Amino acid sequence: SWAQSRDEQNLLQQKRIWESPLLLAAKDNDVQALNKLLKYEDCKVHQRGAMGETALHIAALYDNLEAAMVLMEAAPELVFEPMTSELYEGQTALHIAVVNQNMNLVRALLARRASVSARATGTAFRRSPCNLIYFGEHPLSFAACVNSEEIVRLLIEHGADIRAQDSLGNTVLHILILQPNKTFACQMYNLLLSYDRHGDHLQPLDLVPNHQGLTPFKLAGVEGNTVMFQHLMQKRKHTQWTYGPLTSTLYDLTEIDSSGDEQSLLELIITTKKREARQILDQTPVKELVSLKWKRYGRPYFCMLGAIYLLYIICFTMCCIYRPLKPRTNNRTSPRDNTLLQQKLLQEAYMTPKDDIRLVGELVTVIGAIIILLVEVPDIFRMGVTRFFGQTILGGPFHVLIITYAFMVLVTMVMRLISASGEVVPMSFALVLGWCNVMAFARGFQMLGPFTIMIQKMIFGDLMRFCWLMAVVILGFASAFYIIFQTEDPEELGHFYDYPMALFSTFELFLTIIDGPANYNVDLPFMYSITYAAFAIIATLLMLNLLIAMMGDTHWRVAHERDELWRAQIVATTVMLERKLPRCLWPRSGICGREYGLGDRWFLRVEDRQD
Amino acid sequence: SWAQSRDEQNLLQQKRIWESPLLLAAKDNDVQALNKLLKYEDCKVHQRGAMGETALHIAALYDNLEAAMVLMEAAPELVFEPMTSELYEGQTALHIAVVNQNMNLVRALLARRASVSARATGTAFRRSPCNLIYFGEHPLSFAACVNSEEIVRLLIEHGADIRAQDSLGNTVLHILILQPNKTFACQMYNLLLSYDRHGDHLQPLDLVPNHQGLTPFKLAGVEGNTVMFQHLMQKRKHTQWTYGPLTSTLYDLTEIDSSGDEQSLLELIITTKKREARQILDQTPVKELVSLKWKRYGRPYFCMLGAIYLLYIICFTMCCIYRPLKPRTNNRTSPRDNTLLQQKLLQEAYMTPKDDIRLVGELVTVIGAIIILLVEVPDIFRMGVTRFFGQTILGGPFHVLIITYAFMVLVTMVMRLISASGEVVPMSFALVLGWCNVMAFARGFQMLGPFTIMIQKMIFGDLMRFCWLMAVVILGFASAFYIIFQTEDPEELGHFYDYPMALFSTFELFLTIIDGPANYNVDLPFMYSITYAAFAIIATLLMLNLLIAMMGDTHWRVAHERDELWRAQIVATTVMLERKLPRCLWPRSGICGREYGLGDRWFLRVEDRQD
Ligand SMILES: NCCOB(c1ccccc1)c1ccccc1
Ligand SMILES: NCCOB(c1ccccc1)c1ccccc1
Ligand SMILES: [Ca+2]
């Protein structure tokens, strides 16, 4: 219950101004009552409000230069007094001066030589969803947000440093990026480029990283400020000759492609969470770049890894179906004559000329697990375990269960060396999601991907949400069937002889898979005949409602936004096999420079056609 | 990896201008540095760039007449020097002159009497999807594309030949057709008609074929430049009397209908691949023309061929169900008591008075195959075998399996003369797609067609795309069921006694047909009870997702574009039974001329109503 303290103190603002007749005249334009306040006696200049205010704080906050200049002969040092703490740590009147777009107080508090080096790093000033705004803390950082032109010109003419950085290391240029009024603040980008003039030996400010290592170029990408990205792009592209309707411009491509792990661009559009950012893939240098990364040595060296993979599964299944598999030897099946099993999975029979063939069929698989184990000993070391789930679901949640493939297929070889009876429990799991993970490769072969994308987005958000609701409407009828047939002999009509199978038999009855029980040779008890019917009108309702649960997402799908999610998925493939596959088979994308007056920067061009 | 060489040489353009101070001044407006370049010494006039450039090439390409005229006293012969090779084979400054819409250099390089006979047949200039533009190679061919009026007037006043043809034989008039800015280039059609004046004895240019035999009338049709087609149509139609709101105009109809195999119009809208072309059927002379070809002696002589066809199938099925069919005579069924068969298909029993009736019931069918064999001995000779598949899917993919009907129904008579045991393997196939091909005739009977059209577009693009995805999610569970019931006796619960039926029994379980395997008399092994359930929540997912896989196409369907695909399908019928059925029963469409001051051209009229 944190946010209550915001408001408790904010009414305490209205408390302290209420008791104070000086601050009562700081509310409105009571300059003639300010004449009644300062010339008649010595009131102290430190009349602190709820979080430590003075008059020109309150006066400029309630839009009053007329109350602001009359304290100047009263107290010139109160410009040097910031607001105290805990929400507004270091806030001065200069900062709220530009909040109200002007009052000409900006020259007037600069007539008391106010300091732009004041940093208001308080609670409400850092980036958080509990604060509905974000501004940085330097005053010129605020003036970029408010889109007030000559105000920015005014303070740089009085000693403003543009290269100053926030609590996170973001300069003022980052702060212009994170404004939700995007094109309306775009015009102040090049204005703040216009005061770069002294070229520092480290940066001309547009390559400045923050303490999360983001130059504000790609910070616009990882936030997805799309229209600002283009205006930022146009200075960086190097256009060559134009040929009538077409133009052979030439894009920069320095930080865009993967280079030596400097947190390159493409992995950051993947690993972010804000889904408006993925529309940066619809921008002119980027969509065609990933196309050539996907057309040439994209899918055919991807699907080649797919091609060996189902062969790995085929050589798994043949060494899965041929099993030790002896006849029934220890005992006859005594209990109940229900133990309908005879096979018992042999201890140490391998020397036959069939069992050598399965052995080379075997150990290729368990070593093949250890290959995809060694994929993850750096990769679990890379992005943790618990937030690795936070890496999964957005792009490749098929990646995680190929590892639970490996846990089971390793433990079943541990199982065969011990030869315990519980052998099928891995071998069930180790077979089914082996095949179920070949649909991860459906993205590579064309036109087959997007349903498998839509497979993903229906199961993890809708069907498991449905399976919450479905797993309780069963348990009524299932247990209601279970008690209603405790009365009856399970010799005939034996679906419900005990409670654990009574759930399962109801469950498969729920999907209308089983015939619907009914002897028709004896009588059935009376409430069976309606409750099963009372299950039926539910069975025709909610799975039919589940059929249309699909549709309310599907109108939000393909007509609008699965097609982007397909190619958003294709690049989550792209940087990841770029990373995991080492060099000397991938040549990195685009043309290299260094032979053409360009140097170490590699480039990429495209044609077009205008009007 | 071909397209890399485009860019490697295109940076080499920027390499050669970089080393050359003459070409450095050819970049921008360095005429005072051109004073520093030519008057002071004799620099050679052949300073070749990457693919062989000179200065006025580079100057006019970077929009500089001011650099262009200063080399004229330096080198007047460099107009006669084309760009060298391998991309731009024969490109001169005259060609790039009209690319930049003007510079008044067009008169100025004609002051050195430049040649419009220059043909730039280089790599980037022919029609290809690797080139984003298409222009032809004569300079007047370029000026039609750029839509620059008096520029076209200027060069014809200096010796331009309009009748010149490209590498493919297309003249300049074809080049105006293939511009993607369609109405914006439409105004230059009649302008280039306006300089026809000398009537040549062969053509007045608007009947010129190319080396694929396309007069640029129907070339607009086969590409589907719809709005240009109408403006091209209006001069060709011959309007008669107007009666207030109605007008009895009279359309030309020379090349539109099928005539003596001169690659007529209607078959070309069918056999093309670009699906924007089929909207030429929505144009005023064409839609009503095919209507009268379909209303009168269209369907009733089509459905008549349908009417004999199911009678052929009925007289096939009666000679399919009555079979030789002897009792069990060679041996008792010894193995396993599973060989539940007794019939063995008699060798040479035909003389009974029932078996003569099936014999006349027989040989009508195998001869009836040979009729639809003789349809194809010219037709396989017509359009090949492998690209005949490229004829199938767009219109009548039902046509191909009536031929695999014929292969099987021929081989089963080969089979009865040998009387091998494998008799049902054709007879299964020869029966099922015999009936399944009567739905080809669903297009003829009204309102029944479009679902059978939608049958086609769901199976060959979506369900076989689904059956990729579905055939792997089965094999997990199916083999997982197969290993989990290797343990168990297949006497009771015998769905999965071996692997080949284990797939099929899972497959029909997947569509929730089979009952779902459960004895309820014995115990079942433990991972059966969840993995079958783990099959169930997939079984309620993806075939339910397949249900809505239909819908994302269906919103792209009937609300917008199946109704055109229906009548696009009806004319693919129309020219084909026009072709395959010979004369003396079809009278060719429209009214004949030759009695009415019109001659050999046959015509067709229509009424209307305007505002
Ligand atoms: N095979 C290793 C799994 O890695 B996958 C993956 C790796 C990093 C981030 C997200 C997913 C994956 C890659 C392509 C397709 C499916 C999954
Ligand atoms: N019966 C011969 C098959 O020819 B069909 C056909 C012929 C040429 C091109 C495409 C298809 C066909 C014609 C009408 C309906 C269905 C198929
Ligand atoms: Ca049943």
Image (spheres, coloured by chain):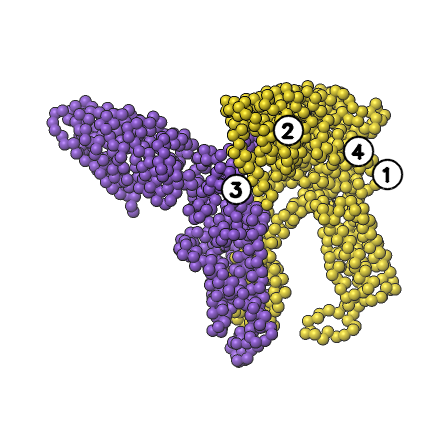
Chain colours: A purple, B yellow
> Spatial distance from mark 2 to mark 3, Cα to Cα?
31 Å
Say what secondary structure mark 2 lies in: loop
State which mark lies toward you, 3 or 1.
3
- Identify which residue, A173 or B291, lies in the foreground: A173
Q: Are marks 3 and 1 on the same chain?
A: no
Q: Are marks 1 and 2 on the same chain?
A: yes
- Identify which residue, A537 or B260, lies in the foreground: B260
Q: Is residue A76 visible?
A: yes
Q: Is mark 3 within 8 Å of ligand 1?
A: no
Quadrant of residue A198 in the image? top left
Chain ID, mark 4: B
Give coordinates of residue B353: x percent, y percent: 87, 62
> Spatial distance from mark 1 to mark 4, Cα to Cα?
13 Å
Q: Is residue B450 left or right of residue A224?
A: right
Say what secondary structure mark 1 lies in: loop
Q: Are marks 4 and 3 on the same chain?
A: no
Q: Are marks 2 and 4 in contact (CB under 8 Å)?
A: no
Q: Is residue A537 above or below residue B490?
A: above
Amino acid at pointer 1: Cys
Disc 2 marks which residue? B81
Q: Residue at 68% x, 37% y: name it.
A: B278
Amino acid at pointer 4: Ser
Q: Residue at 75% x, 75% y: name it.
A: B332
Say what secondary structure mark 4 lies in: loop
Disc 1 marks which residue? B584
Picture disc at residue B589: 4
Q: Is residue A500 above or below residue B429?
A: below
Q: Residue at 68% x, 40% y: name it.
A: B273
Disc 3 marks which residue? A591
Q: Is residue A51 left or right of residue B535?
A: left
Amino acid at pointer 2: Glu
